[PDB]
Amino acid sequence: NNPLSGLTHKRRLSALGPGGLSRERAGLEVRDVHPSHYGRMCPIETPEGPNIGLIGSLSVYARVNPFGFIETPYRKVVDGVVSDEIVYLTADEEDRHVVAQANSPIDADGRFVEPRVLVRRKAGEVEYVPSSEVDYMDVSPRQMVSVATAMIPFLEHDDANRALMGANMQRQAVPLVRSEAPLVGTGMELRAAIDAGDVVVAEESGVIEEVSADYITVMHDNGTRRTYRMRKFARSNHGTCANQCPIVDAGDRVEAGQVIADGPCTDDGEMALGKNLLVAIMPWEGHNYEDAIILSNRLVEEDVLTSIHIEEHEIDARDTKLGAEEITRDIPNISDEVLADLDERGIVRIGAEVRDGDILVGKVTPKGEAREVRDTSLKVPHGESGKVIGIRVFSREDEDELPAGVNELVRVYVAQKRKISDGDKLAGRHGNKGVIGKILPVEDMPFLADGTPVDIILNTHGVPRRMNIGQILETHLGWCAHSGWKVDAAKGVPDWAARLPDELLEAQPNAIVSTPVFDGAQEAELQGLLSCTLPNRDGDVLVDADGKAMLFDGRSGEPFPYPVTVGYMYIMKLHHLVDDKIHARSTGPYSMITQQPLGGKAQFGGQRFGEMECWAMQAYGAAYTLQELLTIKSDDTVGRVKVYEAIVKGENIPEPGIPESFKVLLKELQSLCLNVEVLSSDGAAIELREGEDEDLERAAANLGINLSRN
Amino acid sequence: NSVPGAPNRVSFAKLREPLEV
Amino acid sequence: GGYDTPLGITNPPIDELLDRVSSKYALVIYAAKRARQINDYYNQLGEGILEYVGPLVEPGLQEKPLSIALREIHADLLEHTEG
Amino acid sequence: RVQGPREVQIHLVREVQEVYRAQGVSIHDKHIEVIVRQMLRRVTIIDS
Amino acid sequence: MLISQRPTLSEDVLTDNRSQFVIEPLEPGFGYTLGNSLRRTLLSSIPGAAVTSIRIDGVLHEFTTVPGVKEDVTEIILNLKSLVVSSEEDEPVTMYLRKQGPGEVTAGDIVPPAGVTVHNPGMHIATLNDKGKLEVELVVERGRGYVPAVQNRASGAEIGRIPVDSIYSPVLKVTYKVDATRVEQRTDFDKLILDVETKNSISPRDALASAGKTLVELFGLARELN
Amino acid sequence: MLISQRPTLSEDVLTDNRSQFVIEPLEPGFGYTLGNSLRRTLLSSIPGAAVTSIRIDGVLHEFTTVPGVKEDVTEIILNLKSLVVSSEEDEPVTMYLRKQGPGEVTAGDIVPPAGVTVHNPGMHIATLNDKGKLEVELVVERGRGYVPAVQNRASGAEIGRIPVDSIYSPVLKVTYKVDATRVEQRTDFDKLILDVETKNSISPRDALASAGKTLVELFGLARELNVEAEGIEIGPS
Amino acid sequence: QCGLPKLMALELFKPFVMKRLVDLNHAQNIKSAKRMVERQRPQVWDVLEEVIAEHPVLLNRAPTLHRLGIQAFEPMLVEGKAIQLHPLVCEAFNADFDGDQMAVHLPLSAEAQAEARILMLSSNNILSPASGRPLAMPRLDMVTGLYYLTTEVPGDTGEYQPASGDHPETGVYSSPAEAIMAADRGVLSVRAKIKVRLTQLRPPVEIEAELFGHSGWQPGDAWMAETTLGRVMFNELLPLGYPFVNKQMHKKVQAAIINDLAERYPMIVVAQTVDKLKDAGFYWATRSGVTVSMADVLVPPRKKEILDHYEERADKVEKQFQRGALNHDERNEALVEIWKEATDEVGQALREHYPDDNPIITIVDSGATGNFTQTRTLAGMKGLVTNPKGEFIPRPVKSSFREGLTVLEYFINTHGARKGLADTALRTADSGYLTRRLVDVSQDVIVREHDCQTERGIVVELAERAPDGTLIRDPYIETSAYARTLGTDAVDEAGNVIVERGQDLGDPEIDALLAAGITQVKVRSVLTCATSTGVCATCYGRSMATGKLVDIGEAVGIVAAQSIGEPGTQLTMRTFHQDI
Amino acid sequence: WLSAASFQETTRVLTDAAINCRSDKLNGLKENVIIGKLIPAGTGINRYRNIAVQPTEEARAAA
RNA sequence: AAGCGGAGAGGUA
Ligand SMILES: Nc1ccn([C@@H]2O[C@H](COP(=O)(O)CP(=O)(O)OP(=O)(O)O)[C@@H](O)[C@H]2O)c(=O)n1
Ligand SMILES: [Mg+2]
Ligand SMILES: [Mg+2]
Ligand SMILES: [Zn+2]
């Protein structure tokens, strides 16, 4: 899906497999968090389906023993002074010492501020003991979390469930066309992109000699030259787009390990999965009821949330007993209006726009008793469209490696751009998730005093009861980062800013800051930064000391009666789009043993009417709806055509018959050596073996199994 | 830090890391 | 009654229709039978006259037979014998 | 065996209702009497 | 008591594209609705001109690259999406862009026909290193609102044509401030200050005139009721 | 440019003093720029006349009950505050109401001076039983809107003058709603439904016609900045 | 009504559209019309509009736990690719908009359409078939809007001033129109006590008896009310002949009003009143001013003192254990008791500190969502955490999510979330298996006749005689005596009869029974029916969903199984929320 | 035997039915659903299916 | 005038 999903697919520990466990008969004591997982396996990230607790992720600092046991690094402390020597220990040994906590008050000289410290004892219990017998310490916080869980700011303010959901949903974002980087994030993004492997990094120092959109030529310092090629508009395993772009000039000097080109979801070397949007938190006219989202129309005009998706089609020209199939232009009788895009020898032209039902490659197959031929060309499935990017043709004449009995193989690539629309799914890093319920014009959204409309509206009834208030903290800090600040320290420094590092007392508009996972900004520092923020181009301050603004009403013009919480938030677009989920059917292919419709979208398939829906129908008392559902719409082979004819001609719907499934059941029971019979009111078992009945085919058109030819 | 051309992203962290990832 | 004008599927009100029958299950068959009669009359208009008659109330611009049957039941132009 | 069918019906309905009343779920007793009625419809034959 | 004053309009310039308009004395309470009527009209229905399609020399579709040019076609289109142009003809008009050799292709290298002007002659479009040549053909039309791309086969166009999305409105920002005079004796009124900032393609005084004309035309249905 | 769909205004007469108008089909987003402006202009722009103060003999210090009359001061104020009166003179006009004997004192005994006319003679004001006498002095002026009670200026001179609220506007209630129409394959146009209920002096159609003539002359100010502006034209009728 | 995408509608209605295309001479045969529909010519969207009118569709969402999981709606064409669903039918389906999907089915024949239009319509199913409580009523944002509107705040603008000397009353109004004009000018608030003259709203019982007595012909009879403007605007939404309420609308008050409406009025009235309540609630939830920010989350003023006070006692117990007096279990029990007491004390302090107009407290107090345990966890003190086995860890979590948990406080807090997530995915199988067995056992119980004329029946307690000399209503009396036909005449004191045999036991009957002084009653039950096959409509009693005597032909054996098996499964998939 | 076989333990049920030579009357909900006719509940019972609808004498004469 | 079965893996509500 993106670099993070690939980087996390590896670094995955699985309990299932040959010689392991079972997905159903697993239990409840093996799917739990053990006190020995601290530092070795992340307790937060895991699936929430039937695999919960049976799949996990390695922690950031862990490694693997030669025997196969996981180890973690500890810093050794002797006689009350914390040294700088690191030793890797495994759980067997870690149960023999006393290990302190990562965030303890070191006195800048190797001694703890307060003797009483929380330590982990032998059996995994945590106890408060004087700082006198400790002999090891954690190397740093965030040592117990994985790589995907270390990219969530303000993680210690969220509950475990929503944090797990956010960690899982960060791996589903689709690459966008711009990919800007977060305003407020953690420090883990730069390393998680270089080590994923979706960027180009210089191998040796040199002076860049030439740069284009195709390659980068670097002239090393010892007279050698090296050229890097780039992959443009390359399809991914999941249908997305993989692109790389140079970010160097024509005279710059580079160094070993420096980043040279970008990737799918990368911005200047940092991982970037979403966009920064202006958020107001309030209920609005009921269009954001029950986790729905309201969006602006500037995100469609300016292509803020847009992505490219690619698709691939295949066809083969194989041999057969009656002859050989060949792709050509001389198709049987079909209008010459549809043979226009096809080039001189079959396959379509590059750059041609195609729609559902168009021909891609024209193949003709010998029909059979010459001139006996049939049309089996490659069409475009239902509901698909887009340009044609490339065509790949293999042949047996030029000695190409192909399976036996195939002379030619053709693949066609089709790409399309995709804008945001109602039904698409959005999410945040803190477990937020919803679908777009409405898209509003720009001129009827709440706007600030200077006239800037908001971009997205999030309801206020879902925050308090889910226990994820890291999002409002992120909103406040994002507003402060966007606008900039300056702490006034002319006469001393404020009491709340004593611990703030210098160079963090002043910021310029559109700054980028970092908040590590378990030690970042406190609420005192945030409350202090909210009170010293720079004004806009006019001497105006839009947001007060509480992080709330006064908005206007876009449809009536009257200001709202109370101030509202406004800020900036990082939103990502998930790969659950409503274009891959809409489906409808009236008549199509059927099965073979039982004559019921096929299932799925790939083939025109019907929806299963299960057992519990039958219970509901029987409880309602609807005796004709159920009978019609189970006989003429599913299984009655003779009632389907009569129903179609009656509907087309406007007469009354006839009565059902006997479905095929009952007949198949009777045949199987007889095949088990059982004498099943259907009796009449006076004996004389019914024949129930068809007969010489009307065999007429009216209505001409095929009921729907296949399409209709001109 | 430690990467030749990384962008500047100031941090709120108070502690020091003896070991790199 | 003190209600606004019903619109769409909610006209005629079911509270009035349910006083013409003894159960909610008899109304279904009542309306379905009358609708089938109306459709049979309609689709054989050009051929030899049939016994079935209707509609008894003036139909709309283009109304499906079931609405005609319900509006005839409401107007008390039919009678049924439960079996 | 000791008291009789009516005591069994009372006991069954009350015992089933206690569990659902603890959690805060309301079900009219007439829904638990069809099942219990269906559980008492047979007899064991002693001498034929 | 009946007020004999009548509302008046005054202007105050802050820059070449920002302006303020003052209206007074209005009735008490009739200050936000008037401002919002004006603001809703200004942000939707001001006619303008925009590009409608482009055609490059050696490219057949959008998902490709040009030799010697540092950007692909898609981000060249995204860069062109922010060109400010104006015209007064009532038919599509074609503009040419030609560049060769090392340099930087900007919006000032476009040669427009008579009647078309480019008000953003310093923006950046592409960079050509040593062996890149750019030859682009643009089409300009007039309209209003936002109109997405028009598919190629709908209009029966050629194969190298690349439809682009178009935005016509020449207004950037609008806001209002209402000053109340709520005192005793029942001698109340309002002041409205409307601040308008345009795209440099039309003076902020003409956008207001167009909006006023639209609204005066539209509010004439109720008057004919006589 | 041309809209290509001329809007039309309908009307539905619910009652002699209450109507519903419908405007359709409006271009997308134009049902909200008309509804609020029309409502405000109808409610607080059309001039009228109303009572501004009253003076009752006898009741000077206490403001609880007036001897001889069953009703109290508040009921009298409420009954007088719903008078439908119309005046053409601009200066304040003083009218006298005098009643004696046992009977129901109604609005038909106001005997107004020249110009002012009472449009609802049959309105109950009070009822005298115990040989009580009513002598009331009323002040009538002109204005527009809902000018509330004004604090008495010359309190010492006119001690008993009781100021009241004023309902100058003939229109009493207005509401609006916006729905969606198809108009071709668009499916997302707008329709505006406006419900008006007036007092017994003007008709809803006349009120709507008078409210759309103070809005043309309000945006004429903006249109006079530049006469040739290339706006939008609905076209000839 | 429901919203249907144009593409789905065009694909489901192909035969009808082809018939209409041939009829209007837009095509020449049935092969021409099928191609015209397949290529989607502009001549296909003209007829689709009038071919789907008055043709209902069935909507379904899985799992279908009870009857109301399938419902019939009237479709309307919309632009887009998502189905639009009414806000009020999200509790029957149990659907929320974060990625859910639904299935659509189409009836064909005349009987199928009649059943979908008469039996399964969504405007006819408003009451729950298991308890009779309404299911299509305001919830969430609508409750907040209706609770904000109908509230009185002392000292607000324009409040009634009962003074004398100079200004007589200063706050009495002549009609709601004048009050609305004053509110528009900004000199009044919709939550300030005033006195109005109402003429189109019926007075309460006591006022009606005292003022008019005979009959309050409300069309034109006037009275004076002492209330707020929001309450008048709320009462202008209920039926015309409904007495003035004048109360603040907690959720229970709205539920009781809906119940009374459904009990005394036809179905169209209730279906039309719920929509008006929805509109008003959505309109006023935006103006309510409920927003969440880090400043709204207040903290107890004295948490440090309480925590140190209890920490001293915990240290005392630990020292006593270390000396050698206590064993392990006694120490654990002492620590657990101390820490539970400390958490309760901090919770009480927090509850006492909060103001009354905070959004955090207002949302929970109005009955909209959430409890106070979550508020204490967020702003107070998380408390004691459990073990993997289920025991209590002696060390508590002394910091809330507003301050931020430490590393091992955040680690030992993950034991309790994994267990909930894992049980939710493992108990549903047990619930479903039990439900299937229940449905299979009792699939043959159907109402067969009208009366078996039996003399048997069960005895219900129906309240008890208090020792002091009074009667206390039995706590659970709406699940044992309500909605059951009487079996024997209720004779009291051997003087007369209150309720005669064969009478349904509603609210008035129970109240009269208690007033007369009858404690124990005899009712007819299904356990003692005398019909050979199935049951009869008189022993079963009143239908919980419709309120009338049950119809002949009902399948009362499947609804019983569904009613029993729905809550268990549903509460299995909400474990950590609030076990089963 | 059809309902019992479709509930659980199909093999044992079928073996017992074959040995005993049982016959099924087909008067339930499961069996009617399986073979494909109207269930004996709701609008499927005789008193509701066998309904006769005809216009009244006065209305018929009027038209 | 023409085809559509099994095994495994990962996801959504
Ligand atoms: N294995 C599964 C998982 C989910 N579901 C279905 O999806 C929903 C999960 O709700 P949910 O827990 O995601 C939120 P909700 O239940 O609405 O509570 P809240 O609003 O207070 O947050 C349930 O209603 C189930 O019917 C299922 O059938 N089988
Ligand atoms: Mg939910
Ligand atoms: Mg859901
Ligand atoms: Zn019985």
Image (cartoon, coloured by chain):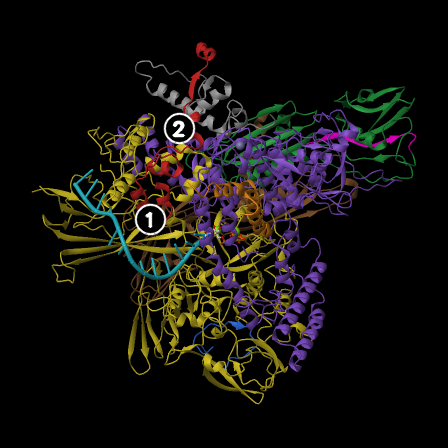
Chain colours: A yellow, B blue, D orange, E brown, F green, G purple, H red, I cyan
Residue A540 visible in this rendered orientation of the protein? no
Q: Residue at 44% x, 36% y: name it.
A: G75
Residue F138 in the image, given as x and y percentages of width and height: 83, 29
Q: Residue at 63% x, 59% y: name it.
A: G373
Residue A610 visible in this rendered orientation of the protein? yes
The amino acid sitting under disc 2 is Ala
Give the residue pinned by disc 2: G110
Q: Secondary structure at mark 2?
A: helix
Residue stretch rendered in magenta on the structure: F46-59
Residue E212 is one of the magenta-drawn residues: no
Q: Chain of mark 1?
A: H
Residue F158 in the image, given as x and y percentages of width and height: 90, 35
Q: CA distance from mark 2 to mark 1?
A: 43 Å
Q: Residue at 36% x, 38% y: name it.
A: H31
Residue A306 in the image, given as x and y percentages of width and height: 41, 55
Answer left or right for C61 relative to A491: left
Of residues F36 and G72, the one drawn nearer to the viewer in this rendering: G72
Answer left or right for G237 relative to A680: right
Asked if A433 appears above or below F180 in the picture, the reply is: below
Give the residue pinned by disc 1: H12
Q: Secondary structure at mark 1?
A: helix
Residue G356 in the image, given as x and y percentages of width and height: 70, 54
Of residues A599 and A108, the one drawn nearer to the viewer in this rendering: A599
Labelled pair 2, 1 in contact (Cβ < 8 Å): no
